[PDB]
Amino acid sequence: QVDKIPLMSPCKMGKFELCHRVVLAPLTRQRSYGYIPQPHAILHYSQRSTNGGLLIGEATVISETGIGYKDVPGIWTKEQVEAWKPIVDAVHAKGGIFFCQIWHVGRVSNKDFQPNGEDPISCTDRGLTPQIMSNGIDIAHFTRPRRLTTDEIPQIVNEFRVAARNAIEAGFDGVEIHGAHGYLIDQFMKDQVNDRSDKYGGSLENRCRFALEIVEAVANEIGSDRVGIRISPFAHYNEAGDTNPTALGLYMVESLNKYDLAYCHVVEPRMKTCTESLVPMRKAYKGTFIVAGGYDREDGNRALIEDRADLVAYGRLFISNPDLPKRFELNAPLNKYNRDTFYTSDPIVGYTDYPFLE
Ligand SMILES: Cc1cc2nc3c(=O)[nH]c(=O)nc-3n(C[C@H](O)[C@H](O)[C@H](O)COP(=O)(O)O)c2cc1C
Ligand SMILES: [Cl-]
């Protein structure tokens, strides 16, 4: 047989007993027509479920104002909650642990996606410059956001709280707060975006206030052992960089310690220039640490051997390998992924048609 590897080692996380450390990263696939989870997702998630394996669902919108892309699922209506149930049930049928990633795009939207054509909301009133859409043909334009007022913010915090409850109602084992990639929560944390002059800005502490109020509200709502949060301190995605990423990341993990969460999920920096690294954050964080961003089998085992993380989340390789955990375990060849169908809308093509090991 093949030598055992750290990636296949059981891991205790929060109140859960995982059977291995290969995690399905959150992956927006834009196949949730009308913002409603679809039948084909039942198969998609089921194909990737393993006994005791952790699955993090695609970013799920917490309210009407959090929409910034077509066909992404939401979880603010009964219809969406009910549509989520069969998908969650399929994952549970195979013994998987399923966390719902709750999300709000903030300024990364257009009034055409908004209720009554309203302006997107954000920590600031500055908009994004145009971006080339996933199809590589069309250009996405964004509407300048309306700066949320100090007293409006708690209402948004409550939207995350309600979304978390709805996820529990749908049967999810827990929720992951989307505090990354320049979306609403990251907009408040990043100093290139947050130019507020009230208590939600002006200092590292103030910029992280929003994220921490969300953690508290969500943790108090469903229990901290059913809560995780994802951050990307070093990412500049959606024009959301920070002048001191290391300090930002350190402050967040140190502040998150007191909440006793199920885990903290951090994305690796794209480049190393003090220097960008997740090691200091792993050392400062006392709970379960999940890393993601460019990992393969070799790097995944190495991260565990060097004790840089407890869990390793895989995105692209999991898109093309339903049975990624098994393949890693057998050190089997991997299917290549086709980025051209990552965000296309077919129920099957590039979604459920990647083959299992022969
Ligand atoms: C098609 C696609 C969709 C993604 N959707 C999300 C998402 O909804 N939420 C999120 O936090 N990250 C999202 N990500 C980022 C991934 O979770 C992960 O961090 C990324 O794939 C980095 O790792 P990899 O080298 O294993 O692909 C997405 C990535 C891809 C390629
Ligand atoms: Cl302000």
Image (cartoon, rainbow, N blue to C red):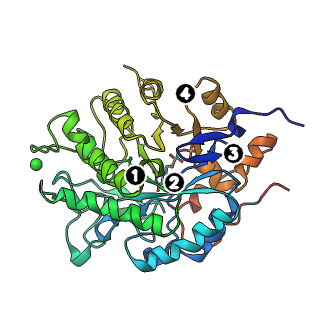
Q: Do the residues labelled 2 and 1 touch (CB within 8 Å)?
A: yes
State the mark number for residue 19. 3
Q: How crowded is mark 4: few (under 14 residues within 10 Å), some or many (20 or more)?
A: many
Q: Distance between the residues labelled 4 and 3?
A: 19 Å
Spatial CA distance of label 2 from label 1 is 9 Å
Residue type pointed to by label 1:
His
Q: Is residue 180 visible?
A: yes
Point 57% across, 44% down: residue? 313
Is ligand 1 less than 8 Å from the beta carbon at label 2? yes
**Mark 2 highlights which residue?**
26
Image quadrant for the N terminus? top right
Q: Residue 121 carries which label?
A: none
The quadrant where residue 127 appears: bottom left
* Residue indicated by mark 4: 308
Residue 26 pos. (x, y %): 51, 54
* Element type at mark 4: loop
| Amino acid marked by disc 2 | Pro
Q: List the residue tagged with mark 1.
A: 178
Pick whichever of labels 4 and 3 is earlier in the sequence: 3
In three-dimensional space, the C-alpha distance between marks 4 and 2, rounded to whole angstroms, equals 21 Å
SS for callout 1:
strand
- Mark 3 nearby-residue class (10 Å; few <14, some 14–19, many ≥20): some
